[PDB]
Length: 222
Image 1 (cartoon, rainbow, N blue to C red):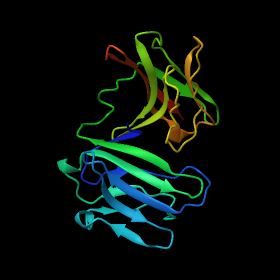
Image 2: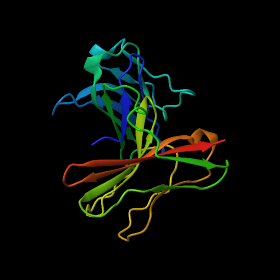
Image 3: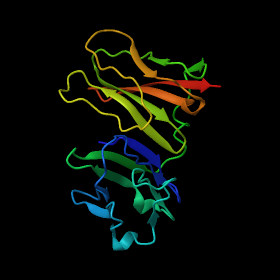
Image 4: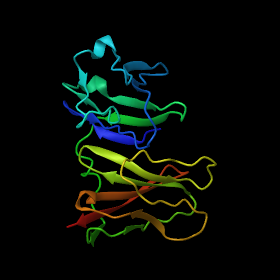
């Protein structure tokens, strides 16, 4: 129901970068208040821009090297009412839409609730293998890989072997994931890792009983 969770802050940014090579035709930023949706912004490559009147002077598009591929939404002065789920919709007709769902939550640093269980050192330029030490059998229903930062948590992979539809990560940096039926090691691979790939990587299991387990790796790439 969400691809990225970011911490509520006065100048928070909802990252959204189109990862595909298709020619863009439109972006839309929406917030799902309830069942109804509020159209925050609509932008077209002809520089036509719709902005919802209540968001007139509340949001902007910093978007380093502005090229309409990066449409991350930044707040000037956010408040508790800005908590909720946002949708960032890229249209690249005829190729079809690419949607990233962002949930804003009231919280402290996400790293607080993710103390590292393992420390992983690796040299730059190598394919780093992250190993989840959590069991995958019943009652566990799905296993999720996330990158945990103080301000945001990005879902890198999600595997539910019973689900017929697969989960596609909206994370910009490429990773190698595998949702296989075998009883092998639950692995996430970071290809050609750099110093920017350092940080907390958390594998998370969700069970049919509702119980939540987590295993956190502190990856350090000098």
